[PDB]
Image (tube, rainbow, N blue to C red):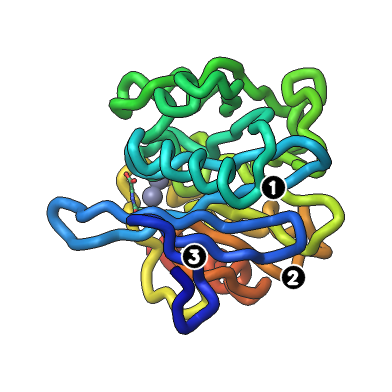
């Protein structure tokens, strides 16, 4: 079902295409106590296979994503990468595993997952001192370039860039350019957030479209605005 802003709504989910081979999947959870909070992930068509970034809030919603891919793209999903251990990102792991999809996550995310009430991914990504993922730990990721910017939204948020496009996924590290706060600061590293935000921008300097978890895709203005807000917080 197409809407005003060019977003196709598919059941309780919403899908928007960002590039010839990149879609953004959006799911909603009526959050206690807040309201209906949106969460964004990515779907990437890489040849004869599909790559998924982040699940939905629930197993059923993630299964709905899988149905959409089967219906709209019709290609086997090779792998999934989840960006950190919160429900909006890892709430539908069982749906992926029941579908036989190999799942990947930061080793710290997999370690933190039980405490965060999550199901861990099946494989662990580790990272070099400069932030880039060990290539041996992220095999055949195609156009996906995974980067750990340091502690920000959580101690474990990783970010993904997509080769061939100008799209980088900041996840819940980056907020939009009109955000007046940084949101859920429960697991946040207020001391290193700003550094992490700028590190992300430096990792993908040629990315002009920044996709984030809870807002529509923004420009690089979101990165500098986030880091600026993170500075204000750190300076008390
Ligand atoms: C404000 C934060 S980033 C949110 O929307 N959800 C946090 C969570 O999924 O646990
Ligand atoms: Zn989170
Ligand atoms: Zn979140």
Badge 1 residue CB within 8 Å of ligand 3: no
Q: Residues within 10 Å of mark 1 (few under 14, many from 20)?
A: many
Residue bearing the label numbered 2 = 208
Residue 44: mark: 1
Task: State the residue in front, 11 or 151.
Answer: 11
> Who's the residue at 61% across and 67% down the image?
223
Q: Secondary structure at mark 1?
A: strand
Q: Locate the C terminus and report the quarter of the image it occupies.
A: bottom left
Q: Secondary structure at mark 3?
A: loop
215 to 53, vertically: above or below: below
Q: Are marks 2 and 1 in contact (CB under 8 Å)?
A: no
The residues bearing labels 1 and 3 have C-alpha atoms spaced at a distance of 22 Å
Q: Secondary structure at mark 2?
A: loop
Q: Position of residue 185 (x, y in %)?
A: 34, 51
Residue bearing the label numbered 3 = 175
Q: Are marks 2 and 3 in contact (CB under 8 Å)?
A: no
Q: Residues within 10 Å of mark 2 (few under 14, many from 20)?
A: some
Quadrant of ligand 2: it is top left
Q: Nearer the viewer, mark 2 or mark 1?
A: 1
Q: Are marks 1 and 3 in contact (CB under 8 Å)?
A: no
Q: Position of residue 31 (x, y in %)?
A: 20, 53
Q: Position of residue 38 (x, y in %)?
A: 36, 59
Q: Is residue 120 left or right of residue 131?
A: left
Q: Position of residue 228 (x, y in %)?
A: 54, 70
The tag earlier along the polypeptide, 2 or 1, is 1
The tag earlier along the polypeptide, 1 or 3, is 1
> Who's the residue at 50% across and 81% down the image?
5
Q: Nearer the viewer, mark 1 or mark 3?
A: 1
């Amino acid at each position: 079902q197409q809407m005003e802003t060019g977003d196709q709504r598919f059941g309780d989910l919403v899908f928007r295409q960002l590039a010839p081979n990149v879609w953004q999947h959006t799911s909603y959870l009526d959050m206690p106590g807040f309201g209906a909070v949106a969460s964004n992930g990515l779907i990437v068509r890489d040849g004869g296979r599909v790559l998924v970034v982040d699940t939905a809030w629930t197993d059923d919603q993630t299964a709905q994503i899988l149905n959409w891919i089967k219906q709209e793209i019709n290609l086997p999903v090779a792998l999934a990468v989840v960006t950190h251990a919160h429900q909006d990102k890892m709430g539908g792991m069982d749906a992926l595993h029941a579908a036989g999809i190999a799942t990947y996550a930061n080793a710290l995310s997999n370690q933190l997952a039980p405490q965060e009430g999550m199901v861990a991914a099946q494989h662990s990504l580790t990272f070099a001192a400069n932030g880039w993922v060990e290539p041996a730990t992220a095999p055949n990721f195609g156009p996906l370039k995974v980067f750990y910017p340091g502690p920000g939204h959580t101690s474990d948020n990783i970010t993904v860039g997509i080769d061939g496009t100008d799209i980088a996924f900041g996840g819940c590290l980056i907020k939009d350019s009109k955000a007046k706060s940084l949101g859920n600061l429960g697991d946040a590293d207020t001391e290193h957030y700003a550094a992490s935000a700028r590190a992300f921008g430096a990792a993908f300097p040629k990315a002009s479209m920044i996709v984030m978890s809870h807002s529509a895709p923004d420009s690089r203005a979101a990165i500098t605005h986030t880091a600026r807000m993170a500075d204000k917080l750190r300076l008390e």
